[PDB]
Each structure stands twice: as structure tokens, then as C-alpha cells.
Image 1 (tube, rainbow over the protein chains, first blue to last red):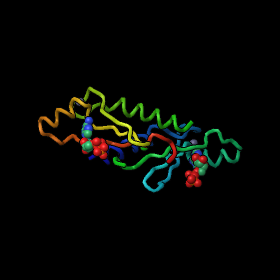
Image 2: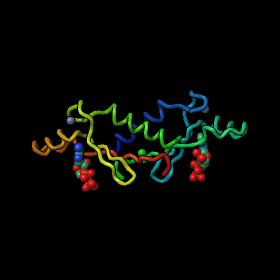
Image 3: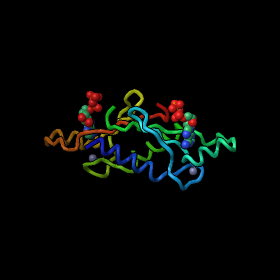
Length: 69
Length: 69
Ligand SMILES: Nc1ncnc2c1ncn2[C@@H]1O[C@H](COP(=O)(O)OP(=O)(O)O)[C@@H](O)[C@H]1O
Ligand SMILES: Nc1ncnc2c1ncn2[C@@H]1O[C@H](COP(=O)(O)OP(=O)(O)O)[C@@H](O)[C@H]1O
Ligand SMILES: [Cl-]
Ligand SMILES: [Zn+2]
Ligand SMILES: [Zn+2]
């Protein structure tokens, strides 16, 4: 079933690319209608970057959660 | 830049999962507004399946080509 191909790719995408800043924790994310937004950083590193005033790694990639648009 | 993360993931997704039927040729695809549709089969296997009357592997997965929806 094609929705499972999409789902399994998303599970994999989320798993193999950890937080861009600390490289170990997995990334923060949220569900955004029919998209999954994967933020570049875990929450700890995100809150940290506000504290240290660095916005270099701020960002996200949205992913349609279904096989068919 | 976040659009490049999306693009590089798509280049990889397309590269490591070949046609579901013959497992060697890369898949057919088309550009569909702001989505990239990756069909489950290469064209040769798709046209073949119509000939042999098998629709088991028919299908596709659409991918938003941008980082931000
Ligand atoms: N964990 C995180 N890592 C990196 N960037 C983040 C993180 N959380 C939020 N951001 C960034 O902060 C901004 C606000 O995000 P968000 O709340 O998703 O926007 P919206 O207001 O459209 O819902 C965006 O630039 C987002 O990329
Ligand atoms: N190379 C292929 N491999 C597998 N399935 C395919 C292939 N080409 C077309 N199909 C299937 O045939 C049907 C028609 O596809 P398409 O032309 O993308 O639909 P639309 O008419 O919405 O543009 C869909 O079920 C699609 O998945
Ligand atoms: Cl996508
Ligand atoms: Zn982190
Ligand atoms: Zn094939």
C-alpha cells in the first residue's frame, strides 16, 4: 500500500538524520494539517540557540504525510 | 538552505529504491505542480504490466519539492 511507503520513508528520514547542532538527539517536529514538519534541531538545541543568539541552524522541512496529493 | 535538504533527500529517495518490479531500472516519475510523483515502476515494467494484465504494482508516491508548505 502506497501510504505505507510514504510513512516508512518518513520514519527513516526522521531516524537517520539527527539534530543538526548536537548530531545526537533526534529533531523536534510537529504535525501541520497533512504535513509533518521536521525542525532542523532538537528542542534543547533550539532553546539554546535563542539563548546564545544564534539563528544559523533555525529552519525545517515539511513532508506530505500521504502518498497522494 | 532548507530547500536543498528537501532536494537532496529526493535525489537520494529516487536513487536507492529502484523499480518495484524489476529492482534494477530507476522509477518513472513526473512533475505535478509543486510535487514530484515517483511511480512504483520504471516505464518498461509499467507498460509490461498492462500487457500481462497485472495491476499489483501500479501506484506512486508524491513528494512536495519544497521545504516549506
Ligand atoms: N527545533 C527547531 N529547530 C530549528 N528551527 C526551529 C525549531 N523550532 C522552531 N524553529 C523555527 O522557528 C520559526 C517558527 O516555526 P513555526 O512555529 O513552525 O512557524 P509557524 O509560526 O508557521 O507555525 C521557524 O523559522 C522554524 O523553522
Ligand atoms: N510507471 C508506473 N508505475 C506504476 N504505476 C503507474 C506508472 N505510471 C502510471 N501509473 C499508475 O496509473 C495511474 C495513472 O497515473 P497518473 O497519470 O499519474 O494519474 P493522473 O491521471 O492523476 O495524472 C495511477 O494509478 C498511477 O499510479
Ligand atoms: Cl514531501
Ligand atoms: Zn540538538
Ligand atoms: Zn522495472
